[PDB]
Image (tube, rainbow, N blue to C red; front, side, top):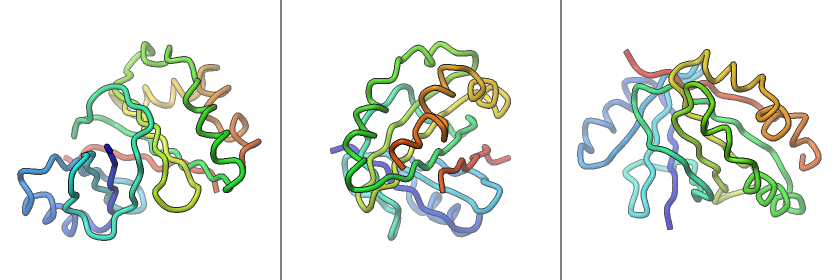
Length: 159
């Protein structure tokens, strides 16, 4: 089963994992509050105590030169199955919006906070998409609150 593993630490800490494990496809980025690294695989991860997720839906490939927004979507044992089906059924049309690169819908291994990655050309492209109806009506705090610390972590490429 394909899973995504995310670890947090300083740039130098995570970059050492990267370079120690060259056979693994690890993507490292700068967030405003921490450095972040992830890999997606159906095999073993090289990360230690990562946050683990099953990949429920995906479009597109990861790239170290893309901007990502990670959306954390809090929910409860009793709302989680309905949240999932809802996020599943969203119209794929966003895939054609300017600057779109990738999408991941992520079911947590522990607890009930769902995660979405949106990959775009740059930050502006994501923030333009975030204002559209396709986003506001499906992926916003307002849109999802009937299934409720919702927040966004922005991930910038490393220079």
